[PDB]
Length: 232
Image (tube, rainbow, N blue to C red):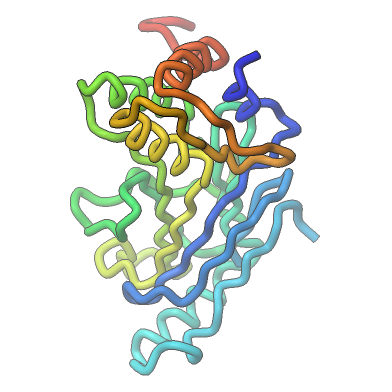
């Protein structure tokens, strides 16, 4: 059996590493595993409480803005997995934007990938393209795929243009993905067996050669959906 397909079975809980930053400063970090995902804050999902800025900030202006955001969070930013997709939904009143990027806090650039919807779930990450890109990476014909989700949380009033200053940023890393990339990087330059920890419930680190890992990655692709051109 392909051990990597365990990543997809419904009963497998993915571990998520959550790191919060206030004006670029790390002020919180926690790693969580929950069947119903998490909620950045009677509702489903493991609640992850962002800390009061008084514990790390000194600027009254930024402290005030952060407290405003803590005030609109309400139900919170929900993030969970369903099949090959990671979904997000803004349950509270804070306009929240997202982007998949590197492990480093992203610059404003061309803006976020999108705004997390409130009335319905919104897809924020598809494991399909990620694995395809990971394979391309192992082939040496592509860059390492990104897996870090960044959530910029603004106020309820849509005129603070939060993505510009990115005062409240929360990075969510599904650790299985970080591990898969590291395994490709390390294994790609090694003729020996290397260990990869999938960081999913009831699992043990896997010892695989580069050839084994590549074969499992290729087979993993068959366990996910890829929309065809013009397919209904």
